[PDB]
Image (cartoon, helix red, strand yellow):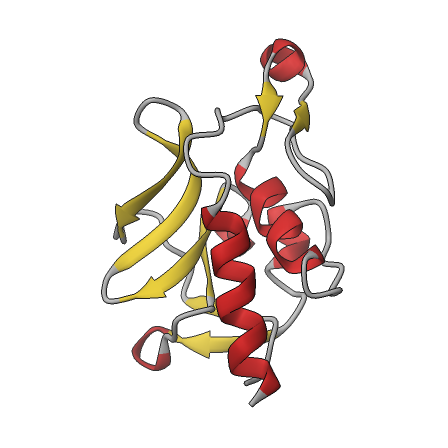
Length: 136
């Protein structure tokens, strides 16, 4: 499917920003941008910002805020979690959002060393549902 290929593309595109620093409020549709607050001096990505930039690469525009990204596709139960599914943290996903790589790995903007990186999926705070944007 084209859906499966779009997701690989999205993931790969996000992956191309590996190491780009974390920046609160940072991110555009075309790449890292200066954030705001303490992000004012860093040209990078916050969590939701990376996600957005990734999906922009296949032409899908998702909201700026992880809480609204949470409601931007279909809610998936943890046990149906799929590579390409968005992972949320905090009530209604208001705190963090990351990309599920499959295999208990995720891609996220704020990893130790405040950079885009690959981490094991974490349990504390995780919202009940993932969100599928692309229905491959």
